Image (cartoon, rainbow over all chains, first blue to last red; front, top):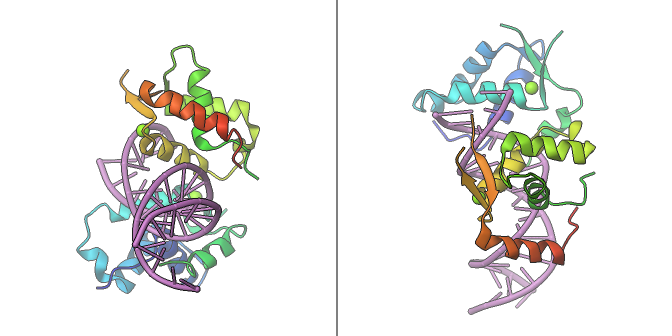
Length: 87
Length: 91
DNA sequence: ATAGCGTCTTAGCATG
DNA sequence: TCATGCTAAGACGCTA
Ligand SMILES: [Mg+2]
Ligand SMILES: [Mg+2]
């Protein structure tokens, strides 16, 4: 139960990159976060809301053509480096 | 890249250009978009930096009338003027 | 979606 | 040389 130094942008990024189809709906993004980080079981209930806000307004996440989310090809490398610059 | 005006200068020029010297945050977006077309297709984070500058800077006071109106604190105004006449351009 | 305030990094300058 | 502090600035994120 560590504290993840990554933002919710990097947690969503790693969950989608670990999927077989490189895409996930908002449900499995929750389940991937709880598994690899049991920290969010003791966190306040609003943690699921903050990842939807990031999923919706971040330039790095788009929907494919309960829909499915994926990584945007333009700002993809912005996320790989955002995970190398995390404190 | 970014226009040569700082976010504090962009907010100051938008409020002073209004008849009541008071604006909500949505109207500040509309003034900057029409006077600077770069932000129409810019990354969406620029609106976040606008609201961040309003809450952080002491020279921007919150006033009441759904958000709230924003104005320029009078006792911090001519300090902001001299800072903007000393460095009028900041890319 | 919006509005308020936040975290993080960077930079020049500055003091120990 | 170094560390530490100050100040403004902004890209980007969180919460209600
Ligand atoms: Mg999005
Ligand atoms: Mg203020």
